[PDB]
Length: 190
Length: 190
Length: 190
Image (cartoon, rainbow over all chains, first blue to last red; front, side, top):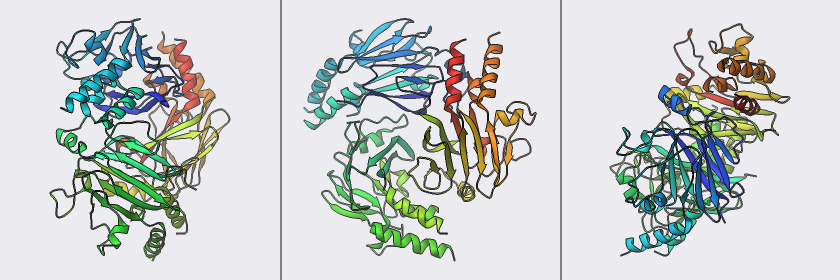
């Protein structure tokens, strides 16, 4: 159904750097690292990208993204993250929120090196959007359910010196295409 | 001749949001709405796009783009707009300027809900660019003749609190490819 | 090996304008000019691009890019520049630095009208990255070796009123794909 199972935008603080990477449905697994190969098919390298506003602090952090992470889509649209770098990663995920009994969105999840964790569930997502839309009928919030965000080196949130992800030196925002298609359908039945 | 009959860039105030959408010549009609399907072929959805600088005022306005508009290319490059939302749209068009006896560029045209209006004429455009180039010979101005701009919710101009389109919360700039090809030819005969 | 032998980003001061142009390996020669054809395959036109932050000074300079330059890839990845405009061009190239006995990066090279000069050598590049990486083992610097930058009208550097290229009204940054692939390999053997 989707041409690309996802599209990824990389940011350094509140600036988007480089262009959006679109992962074909033919690449179930995509790696995002600090390397430099621009060929980009099933691997999105952040090391060769320029940013005229880059600071030494951002360059310092980019040094630590190393092997980065692998994003894997299982089935129609279930998503898993595998932390390949030797530095912990920080993920914003509604699925992980629920699985931690944390209030929706009110949590940043630290994924340790070598960790292979599931970060999104399609069906759960579909159920939640229908219920959430239905309750609304009795889109900016609903779309966030189909998006994952990940900071590569600095954690953000309450117990950190950083209030928001846009305050981290290097992060990505992942748009789940199949999830968004379902949301589009839902929105039309409203 | 053109691969894409047009390319569209969406803005929120003076910031371009999302990437440029390119409409294949195979899609004579393209819809631009406030929905969220990212599949984008003959439909450019603005609802799923993020903007780290977005304000509540911009989110309020995006709420009103709804079904948006349809841009249709008739023949080689004649363009028509159909207002699908239940909110009026505001178009900058040299063709509409001439048809309103308004000074070139000195007008913003309000297109009401359900309205199906012609906003660009290829041949007129071709005639005007030749005459205008010829007079110049006796490119920033000439290219504007091949561009349409449209604000989705707020009108701008003299009788409005907004001086320019870049002051509106959500708008698009449409580049007419065939028109630009003709302009390129003209410029080489100068 | 590479799908695109290079990708080019255009800037006006410190703002990237338009999207990145990707040159297929099928187009050994690509022309970058001040014209307006958006078809862009083996020719990247800067004249039809908009920039809401553009100043009259930038428009004045864009007026002088005219026929611009041709970038040619000879063999696997040797690069030559041909100055087609009647205005001199200003290139940042490590290859040209070495050939001028200038300290790496500490030079801006003026290429005069009609000049057809070689600005990059693949093998030299490969040798330098290996040596440079090896010395480091005893990536932001290494990647610059695979990048060419060119200001179209204003020269920058010590003997000019402009300290950096991001201070020029119109310039491009060219990423050499094959060179970057070699660098990626090198980095993995570290």
